[PDB]
Amino acid sequence: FVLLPEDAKKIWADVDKAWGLALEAGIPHIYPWSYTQVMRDGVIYAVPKVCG
Amino acid sequence: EYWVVDYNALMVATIIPYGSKSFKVPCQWRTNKDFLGVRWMTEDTFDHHLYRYETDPNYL
Amino acid sequence: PVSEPEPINMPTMEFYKRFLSLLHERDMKFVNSVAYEILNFFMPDEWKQLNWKGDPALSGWYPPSSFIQPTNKDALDFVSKAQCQILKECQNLGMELYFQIGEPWWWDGSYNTGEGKNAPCIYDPKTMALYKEETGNDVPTPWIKDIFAPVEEHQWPYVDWLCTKLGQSTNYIRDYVKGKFPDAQATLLFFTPQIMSPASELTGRLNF
Amino acid sequence: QLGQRKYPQVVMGMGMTSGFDDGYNLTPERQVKMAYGLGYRDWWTTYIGMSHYWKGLTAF
């Protein structure tokens, strides 16, 4: 849950870490909480750059 | 498909398209001060950054 | 509001009729959820949970919103009848039924709630009559002024009765929905931080 | 005609959760197609509105 736009890049940073634990835990269905917050912040799923 | 609505918090209204160039706005009126506004936004502030449309305030 | 079969107004129903139609085209199933929270301005006065000073439960949202008392059968029917109206559209479209019970919670003022900063809204006069009618025991006194304050020993029998009564309300709604929708699937949303780390001993013992 | 961005995204195998109180203004057609394009394909959970679904009236 994000709410305030000012904490988007901060909260969403921990969101990805929690997702990895869920994938490790084997959760079959995982959803983001808010459609509004997803579009407000504009989150995407991209492979991290191999630069470093 | 891109029109939006706004109204007083004491009423309920939704917008639903039903044709190529037509749409319906069912609503419920509860108070005398109810004011429903169907508006077209020049700039996009609801869609995703990859789904926004170009902004142009010139309607001449 | 008691004899009305469809509590959901037409514009909301129209939105879901088109909304569910698109989902079926995308072949993704839909899950519905309704809560106990209704707008305070329109909420009936006989359903709001009352604290030790009679102030109905309120939320941090503006306009403020109240919660129904789970001990009220009439209030439970209103919420349950909302689920069947929405799920009826799903059967018309050929979808399978999925519904969620939304936040069963005895309000306690966990966060700021105006005057009721931490006052539990568990002292509704109707609830006291029901507690006396079946348990026979008297309501413990004095009424809890703050959840964080230590709980007296004689307060527990009423607290445990409230905790048990909350489970019946959730079960009652589930049975009512499945009464007309035998193939419907039921679920519930759980707050893990509240379960493991309750705000107070009273909070965890009462609302779980 | 106005320019618009429309870039479909690869499916990540996740669902979408939305609230009615935050989507009444937008048409259902725009919401479903936009979310589907991003990659949410299997599940959808909608939280009913708090003050926008029930019937009501005002009186003196």
Image (cartoon, coloured by chain):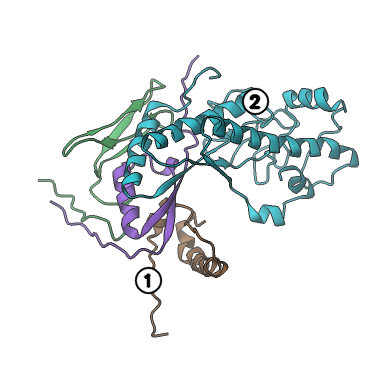
State whether residue D53 appears in this view: no
What element does badge 2 sit on?
Answer: helix
Q: CA distance from mark 2 to mark 1?
A: 50 Å
Q: Chain of mark 1?
A: A
Tell me which chain appears green. B
What element does badge 1 sit on?
Answer: loop
Point out residue C171 in the picture as x, y percentages from the top left corner.
Answer: 65, 36
Tell me which chain appears cyan. C
Residue beneath disc 2: C73
| Residue pictured at 63% horizontal, 51% vertical | C191
Tell me if residue C131 comes above or below residue A43 in the rendering: above
Indicate the quadrant containing the C terminus of chain C: top left, top right, bottom left or bottom right: top right
* Chain D: drawing colour: purple
Marker disc for residue A46: 1
State whether residue D20 appears in this view: yes
Point out residue B18 in the picture as x, y percentages from the top left corner.
Answer: 23, 35
Tell me if residue D34 comes above or below residue C39 in the rendering: below
**Residue B4 image-quadrant placement:** top left
Crowd around label 2: few <14 · some 14–19 · many ≥20 (10 Å):
few
Q: Residue furthest top?
A: D60
